[PDB]
Image: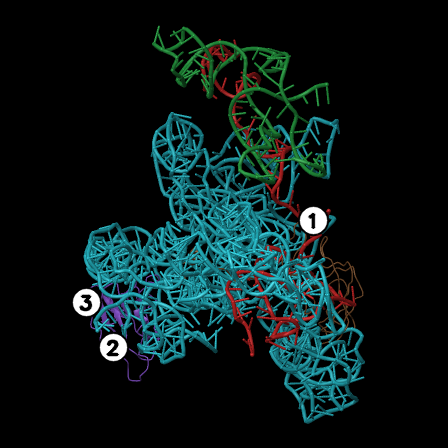
Chain colours: A purple, B brown, C cyan, D red, E green
Amino acid sequence: MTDPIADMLTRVRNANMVRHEKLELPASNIKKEIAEILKSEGFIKNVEYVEDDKQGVLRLFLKYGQNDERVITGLKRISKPGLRVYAKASEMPKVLNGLGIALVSTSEGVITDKEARKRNVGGEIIAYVW
Amino acid sequence: PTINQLVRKPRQSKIKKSDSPALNKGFNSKKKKFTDLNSPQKRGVCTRVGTMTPKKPNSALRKYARVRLSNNIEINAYIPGIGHNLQEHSVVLVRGGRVKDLPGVRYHIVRGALDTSGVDGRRQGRSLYGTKKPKN
RNA sequence: ACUUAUAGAUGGAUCCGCGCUGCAUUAGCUAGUUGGUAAGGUAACGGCUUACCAAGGCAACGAUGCAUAGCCGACCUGAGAGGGUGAUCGGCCACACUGGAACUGAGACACGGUCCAGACUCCUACGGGAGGCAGCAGUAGGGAAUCUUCCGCAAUGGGCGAAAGCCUGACGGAGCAACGCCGCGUGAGUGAUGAAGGUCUAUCGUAAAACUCUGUUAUUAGGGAGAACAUAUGUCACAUCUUGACGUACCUAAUCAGAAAGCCACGGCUAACUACGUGCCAGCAGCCGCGGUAAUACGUAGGUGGCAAGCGUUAUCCGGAAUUAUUGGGCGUAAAGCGCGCGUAGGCGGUUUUUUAAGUCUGAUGUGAAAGCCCACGGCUCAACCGUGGAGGGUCAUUGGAAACUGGAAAACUUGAGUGCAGAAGAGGAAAGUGGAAUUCCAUGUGUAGCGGUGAAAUGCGCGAGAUAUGGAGGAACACCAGUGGCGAAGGCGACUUUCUGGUCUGUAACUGACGCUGAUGUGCGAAAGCGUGGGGAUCAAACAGGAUUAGAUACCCUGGUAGUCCACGCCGUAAACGAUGAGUGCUAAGUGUUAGGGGGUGCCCCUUAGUGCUGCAGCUAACGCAUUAAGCACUCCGCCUGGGGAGUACGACCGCAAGGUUGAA
RNA sequence: CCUUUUAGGAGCUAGCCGUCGAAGGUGGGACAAAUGGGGGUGAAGUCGUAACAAGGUAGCCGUAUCGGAAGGUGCGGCUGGAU
RNA sequence: AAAUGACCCCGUAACUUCGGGAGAAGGGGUGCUCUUUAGGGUUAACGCCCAGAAGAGCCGCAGUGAAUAGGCCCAAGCGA
C-alpha cells in the first residue's frame, strides 16, 4: 500500500478490458487529482473527490464511449516510488504525436499535458492515458 | 530487468573468441614471447608437404601443405585449387584464415608471392592459383 | 651607457576542485590508521624527516594491495546519447648508455657539460680514452613495402653584438611510394551491319578497315610567380644609391596520332554467359553452394553487372549486430528463479497536513575569447594547403521566487497489525508398549514327507525341520478411527494411558497512534543411505554359493547369505527441493468441492475478514496456461539470462569428521 | 670581498670520529619461459544391442555400490510407466 | 679432525593426526670512563640489593677477548 494509486492506475484498462466497471478503489490527495482532471474531457462516470478521511473510498465509474471500444486502450505509469524519472516541461515527449493526454502535478500548482507545453511548469510527468 | 542491483551488480556481453588465434603472430627469440599483431602480410617456410586421404564430402583426391611457422610448433595449411606445386622450402606471402572444409589449418598462399608464380595451366582464371599478365 | 628603491610579465604553478582505468582466485585494520602538538624550510600552509601523547582510527562499502599507465584540437563514425582507437597533428608532461654528480642557474643534476662506480664496437709509447644519430643520413641487418648521405641559408632571429654580420643540422630545398585520392591526358567525324568470323553454332560485330579531328603528353622557345629587407641617408610611425639556386611556373604550341595496364567469379544470392575439355581421373566453392558421360561454376576460350590508374586478396571498429538493453534486457517453458524458519547493510521504504523555503519550475545574471559551433560562406586553374564568427564558450564571475516533494522534519488516522482471544483442527510435533501381524527357532497339546522353490532347475529345511499353533513375554508397530483430510516455509506425516508445546488465527479488533517492504552482513540449517553410542539379526537384501538359457548369462527369476534391516549422543547436503512454480498492489462471472473453525445466522438459506483445489467467463503471454479465490496491467529486491559445444579438463581460492565441495583462462 | 696578510683561540673547503646510505652486488620461494602424463581428440581392422512405444529384462536422474559407452543393483524425488 | 655453541633483540617455509614442525632457516648486539632517568620494596630515602633505554667520548689485530654450552639444507627405504 506504499503507492496509494499504483495498480489502481491501469486498473482503468485492467478493469475495462471488456469495458467493465465493478471495481471500487482507494484514495489520495492525487486520487483527488488522478480522476478529476480528465472529466475535463468527459472520461469518467463519476469521481468528484474522495468523501472520507484516512484516504478512503471512491467509485471508479469509468466512462465508456460511443464506439464501444476501450476508452483506455492501454496504459502504463512510468512514474512510481522506485522509478523516479524527472524531466523538464519543454521536451515533454510527443504522447503518440499528441493523441494521448497527461494529467500530473507541477512545480507551480497542478497542470496537464495541455500546460507543460505552454507554461514551462512540471516535475515527474507521469503517463500516457488512451 | 530491474536497475537497483544493476549498479550493485552488472551484466556481461555475449561470449565469442576471434578467428585464427595461433595466427597474426610473430614468435620472439630475443624476448621469447609472441607478438599480438594482426599483420597484413607474412612469410611461410616449409617443413614438409603432407596429405591425408579420407575425404567424404568431395570424394575426389587432393593433398595439402604442412608448413611450420616460427620456432618449434605445429602449423598446418592446405592448397585450395587445381594447381599442384610439387615444391617446398619456400618464402611466400601468407593468406590468413581457412577456406571451407579443412579443420585446424588457417594459413595459405597468395598468387605469385615471391616463391614461385603458380600452376601455369591456368590462363582464363587471370586471378586464381597463379595468373599474371593475362589478356583481359 | 652603467647599477636600484619599483614594475607590467615567463614557464609555471605554492596548491584547490572534478578531471584522475581494470584485477574479488585480494578486508578482521595500518602501527602512524585517526589528527592536534616541532628547533626546522622551499617565492609556498603543513607528519613533508623529525613534535607530544591515546588508538580501535578501521570496521564486511573496497582499507589496501594491485595490471597496462599520458592526456587532448585528430580520424572511421550515430539520428542521438556520444561511442571507441588520440598514429599523420601534437599546444601540456615520464624520458638523453648506465647508478649517481661537489657543482650550477636572468630558468637544474645538465641529449656532444662536470667527476667517479658499471660493459660495451672500441681509440691510446698501452696519458688510458670515457661514447652510444629516444636529434638527417648510411653500415651488418629484421626486413609487406619501411625514402634522397642531391643543396645550403633566402622565406622567423635565439644568442652574440652602440654596428655592419651569423647558425640553421630549428625551419628549409626533395629520388617521389601510381601510398591518399584527385587535376585531367593517350586516339577521332567515325562508320554501310562491316570479311577474311572468336563461347553459341546470330552472338560482344555498327568488329573492322582508311579517312579525320583535340592539345593535353613531345622538337623548342624568351621564361624573372611575388614582395619589401636595413645606425650614418634626417632627425620607439618609421626609410634609400639595399629582396632571382628551386627564380624557370600560367608554360596553349605548331601539335604528328605521343593508347586507358586489364576486370573478377564467369548461373542464382555477393550482383556472372554459354559451353567443348571431364567421365569421378584431376576437380568447382564469401554464408547457400558444385564435376559420376551435356560443370547455364571447373582447365581454357570472344565478355554482360562494376570499372580504366585500376584486377583477387589483406582485417579494424563503426549505425548495420534489435547478438548491451543510457535510450533498444527472460523467467514455467531456448541458453534462465531460491532448502528456506533464518536474515546485517541498504535499493526500495502507508494516509493527510506538514514544519523545509535547498533543489527541480528552471534564471535574472556572468552576458570573459574561441579558429569553428544546430549553420552557412569568402581567397583559391575546384581538389593539397587559409579565413567573418551573429550558435557566449555551455548554473564558469549571483543567489533564486512555485512547498505540489528525494530534501534541518513536528505529528495525527487506524479497521492494515501483533498479545487478549471459544480456544480448535489435522498423521503439526516430542508419548513408555500393559496387549497384537509374536516372525525363518524348535521337545513340542501335534507328528513326519513336507514350511517351501521356480521363464529353467538346482537352490533348499528332513539320518526324528514339518502343516497351526497349547505356554508364544520378548527384536516392535499401531496392523484397524486412516480419506486426496489437514498443522507447518520445502523433508514429512497414523491407536494413545498421554508425558508436553507454540504460533496459526477463522470474528472484530480493547491498548499504542506507523506500530516500515526483497532481505549478500551474521546464524545458518535441510532425503534413505553418507554420516555419532554400542546394541547389530525379525534376518531378509548387496556379493551373490547355486541351478539354467532359444544360437547365446555370476543375471529382473530362484530357498538361503557377512554392512544395514532392532538406535535416546559429532555435523550435515548432494536428489527429477520435478516444487524445474522466487517473494510487495489490487484485479475485469462467480458459483464451486468444501475446511476444524465462522461474519447474518439455526439437520433451513451462507459470504470471504478467510483457507484450499478448481470447470472455467473476461482479457492478455508466445505456442500454452492462469481466472473474484490470476505468469496478463502498475511501483520490488538477490539477479541471472543474451547462439552452441568443449569447459570444469592447465589450473585454482577458501570452508571443511565424510561423501567432498566451491572456485576457473584457454 | 675570512684578515696575528704567514695565519691562528674559535672559525671556512680539504685529514681525523663519524651519518644515513638509493642504486648496483649477492639473499629466498611467488614469478619464469622455450620447454622439460592427464586429457583433447583421432579419422573406421576392432566394439556392445540398445534409449525412443509394457522396443528386445519399460524410459531416466543423485547415490551403500556401479561401469571398457552400452551394461546391470540396493535406495531419495520420481513416471517423462503401458495395461 | 675442524667448524657451530652462552645471554638479548629482529625474522621464520612446505607440510600436519592442529598438539607440532621451531632454537626452522636467516641476521644483528656485548670492552672502558662519563652523563640522563629506568626500575624496585627489602626500607626511615641513595644506607643494603641491583640492571634498563638514550646519548657522549677512550683504546686494540681481536671486546659472552680465558674455561664450559646445537653444524645446517634437500630427497628416498624401513618401523607409528
Q: CA distance from mark 3 to mark 1?
A: 88 Å
Residue B78 lies in quadrant: bottom right
Q: CA distance from mark 2 to mark 3?
A: 26 Å
The x and y percentages for residue B16 are: 57, 62
Label 3 near label 2: C-beta < 8 Å? no
The x and y percentages for residue B61 are: 77, 71
Name the residue: 80% across, 63% down: B87
- Disc 2 or disc 1, which is closer to the eye? 2
Which residue is label 1 attached to? B29
Q: Identity of the amino acid at label 1?
A: Ser
Can residue B54 be spotted in the picture? yes
Write down the chain letter for disc 1: B
Which residue is label 2 attached to? A41
Label 1 near label 2: C-beta < 8 Å? no
The x and y percentages for residue C612 are: 38, 69
Q: CA distance from mark 2 to mark 1?
A: 83 Å
Can residue A36 be spotted in the picture? no
* Front residue (pair A3, D27): A3
Q: Which mark is residue A17?
A: none
Q: Residues within 10 Å of mark 2 (few under 14, many from 20)?
A: few
Which residue is label 3 attached to? A52
Q: Identity of the amino acid at label 3?
A: Asp
